[PDB]
Image (tube, rainbow, N blue to C red; front, top):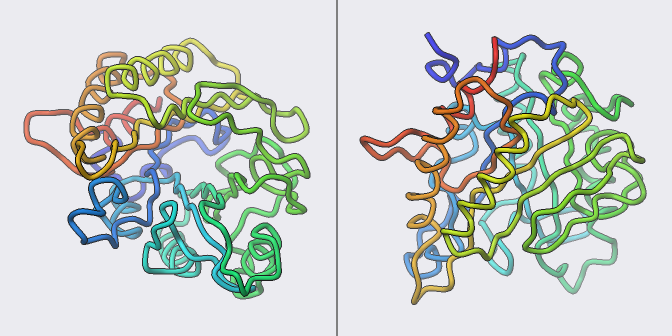
Length: 302
């Protein structure tokens, strides 16, 4: 059977001497937005329909958490202005549970401030994350804390590896975990060095593209990963795109085209490096069309 027939424990079947960078990983964009039900707001604000545990069971390993500091000891999960009805501890507890049941999987968690803090907040978003989550004894042992800038599957499995989109941090483990953080270019394909120059991060995050240009931008970065065997290069390729608003087509409508288009492309490339591909509506299938999460999973070499 191929890896995608067992999406709950697919990383356990790989060689754990691999660097996480060399693994083709399915992520979910604004992972926490499964809570949204409002049909008008959901056109633009909702990007997932499966909860965190169901996403994990479906093979998702990269989680894009964007947040707002709602108190000096709390981060609320957000899409922009829009509160996603739970705090960061919910994601971390779900992750902890999953990883105890599937201990040979790693999860990478991107962390970003998406909206201004509650006006009662006195601390920076990075201080709140560092002090109340990363260093919280409640999540002792859950996070990767090693000093390797380019960690392997073996030293990260059973743990959450920070992908830091907070800016400069005092945290010292994970991607972009230094006092410069990650220089993100807005609505762009870009590359930048991270981890004190140890890694070259290559991103496609052209989130306002219309779908034809979006597909072209995805495929361009997909074509570059394919011929690149450098473990010090890290690819993050977002298939997700903004809706123009509630008058306009939904994020779901776009994903319903982009996902099978990209899944078909990956499948026709066979076993080939993809990078980390971050999708809307992870695990959402359409009869007669390739499934993007499954194809990312099956693109890994055994």
